Structure formats: C-alpha cells, structure tokens
Amino acid sequence: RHLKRELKRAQEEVKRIQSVPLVIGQFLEPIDQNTGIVSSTTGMSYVVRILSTLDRELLKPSMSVALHRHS
Amino acid sequence: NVKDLKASQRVCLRSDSYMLHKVLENKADPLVSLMMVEKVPDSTYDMVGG
Image 1: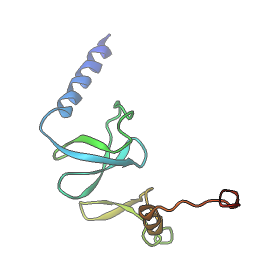
Image 2: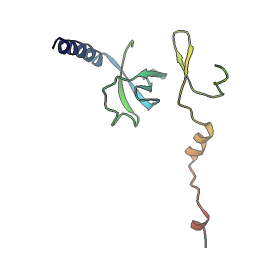
Image 3: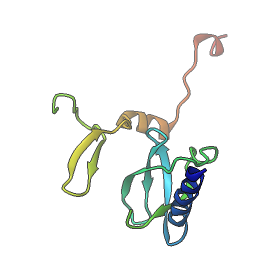
Image 4: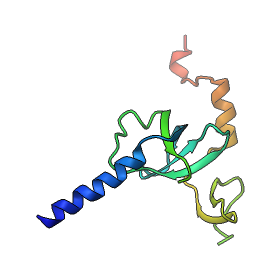
C-alpha cells in the first residue's frame, strides 16, 4: 500500500516532462522501438530514446512528433 | 573494432567529443536509391509473349 503511494509520485514526475516547452521534430524511422531517429527542425539528425508507454500505431510511418529541449 | 566498420556504414556518435558508440542498424545502398526514384518495373517472359 506504501508502494502505491510511490508509483503515483513517480507517475507525476514524468508527466511534467511530457508537457510544454517542446521543440517539434519529425520521426523518420525506428532502429529498435525504444530508440529512433528524429530530424529536429534545426536541420540536423539526432538519435533519441523513445519514452516507453507510447502508441507506435501511427508513429512508425513518418509523422510529426514532440521532443524535449535540453534532454 | 575498426575491422567491423565498413565504408559508408551509418554510425552513432555522441556529440560530447564525437566518440563512436555503436554501429547504427540503418544504412541504404546508394544504388537502391537511384533505382527507386527512377522506378522501373521488371517482368517475366509470359507477360511479354505472343
């Protein structure tokens, strides 16, 4: 019952990273599915980890996407 | 090793000092590129027959 408090405090942390401020890149293709290639909108390629617990149903065909700033 | 890395292999780099981490899975032949933007079907002998 104590660890159900700790799953909630860990779930909060990560939703704040999901949300604004974000730069918009594009997803080219996976190289796994926990790691992919995105081109930011600075005209460079980056290899980025993918937040597990996301829908790859529309993701795998190339399509806009959100990325974190410094991270 | 530099035995594994072959020419025109797309690699991973970590922009901290540009140190090679892994070989990258991806890579396309440059001829697969030129043949596809052209696009030309192939066939068999029976569909060109008569």
